[PDB]
């Protein structure tokens, strides 16, 4: 997941 493919 990771915030929608890049986020945090």
Image (cartoon, grey):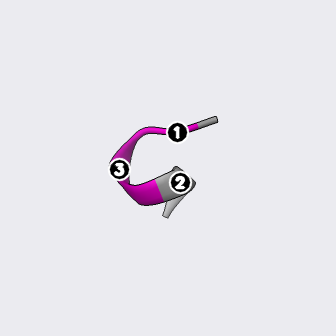
Q: How far apart are marks 3 and 1 (CA)?
A: 7 Å
- Residue 1 image position (x, y, % from top left): 49, 64
Instruction: Please report contact status of discs 2 and 3: CB closer than 8 Å, yes or no.
Output: yes
User: In the visual, does 8 lie left or right of 4?
Assistant: right
> Which SS class for mark 3?
helix
Q: Residues within 10 Å of mark 1 (few under 14, many from 20)?
A: few
* 3 versus 1 height, above or below: above
Q: Distance between the residues labelled 2 and 3?
A: 6 Å
Residue located beneath label 1 in the image: 7
- Residue 5 image position (x, y, % from top left): 35, 50
> Which SS class for mark 2?
helix
Q: How far apart are marks 2 and 1 (CA)?
A: 5 Å
Instruction: Please report contact status of discs 2 and 1: CB closer than 8 Å, yes or no.
Output: yes
Inspect the magenta stretch and tell me whether residue 6 lies in it: yes
User: In the visual, does 6 lie left or right of 2?
Assistant: left
* 2 versus 6 height, above or below: below
Image point 52% across, 39% down: which residue?
7
Q: How crowded is mark 2: few (under 14 residues within 10 Å), some or many (20 or more)?
A: few
> Which SS class for mark 1?
loop
- Residue 8 image position (x, y, % from top left): 64, 35
Residue situated furthest right in the rendering: 8
Q: Total marks drawn?
A: 3
Image point 40% across, 58% down: which residue?
4
User: In the visual, does 5 lie left or right of 8?
Assistant: left
* 1 versus 8 height, above or below: below
Please provide the residue range marked out in magenta: 4-7
Where residue 3 is drawn, which disc sits there? 2
Image point 42% across, 39% down: which residue?
6
Residue located beneath label 3 in the image: 5
């Amino acid at each position: 997941x990771x915030g929608x493919x890049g986020g945090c």
